[PDB]
Image (cartoon, rainbow over the protein chains, first blue to last red):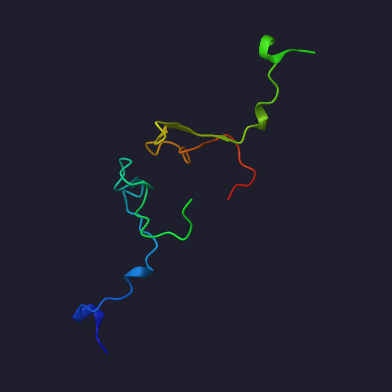
Length: 49
Length: 49
């Protein structure tokens, strides 16, 4: 069928919940209290108090 | 009996679980990723994964 890696037909992006990013095994990258959950990119939620 | 409020005989300090501080209804203190959970000062925990 279509090959998403070559022909750009991506379709599973909704399946990500979050990503965290950390330099030197220690420094949470975006850091600096930037985001409303600062430590990580919480892409979506299941519970939202 | 003793009057802790007047004489200093405080004896219920072991009953606290956690305290959280929030200026302007937004800026959690101390914030800045300082402590292992200080958007809340966790005084004690009943179970410790």
